[PDB]
Length: 120
Image 1 (cartoon, helix red, strand yellow):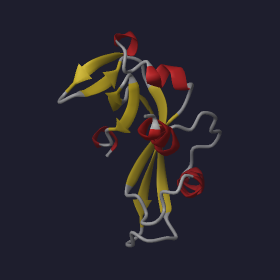
Image 2 (cartoon, one colour; image 1 turned 90 degrees about the horizontal axis):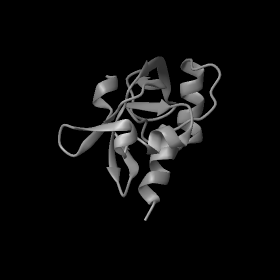
Image 3 (tube, one colour; image 1 turned 60 degrees about the vertical axis):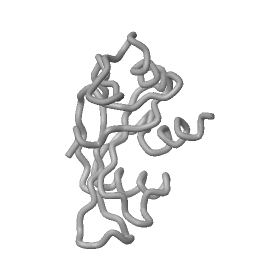
Image 4 (cartoon, helix red, strand yellow; image 1 turned 45 degrees about the vertical axis):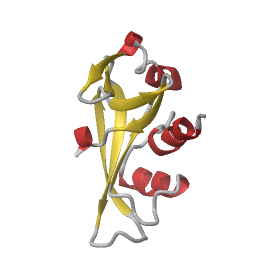
């Protein structure tokens, strides 16, 4: 089963972004189906897939808290953060580009969850 890894890539991987602004967040949150209801906070990781996969191996991760993993290398990221009063669309987002290691959960050497706590 890979359904949760492919879901992870849909929710948290964008390979080649140029501008990582408010409008990027608004756009990509819709492309990936995170707008009914408006998801409160969501972070996309950039670069290649293989660096992210490698977080599950010792090659690029240490264990972390309860059964999570934290990357050794830093990733370019963009956190899209819902604003306005409503959980229902139109969903508008404030973007925060960052550069940092990431925390994921792994299952079968594949990341299936991003811990969003580190990006609040």
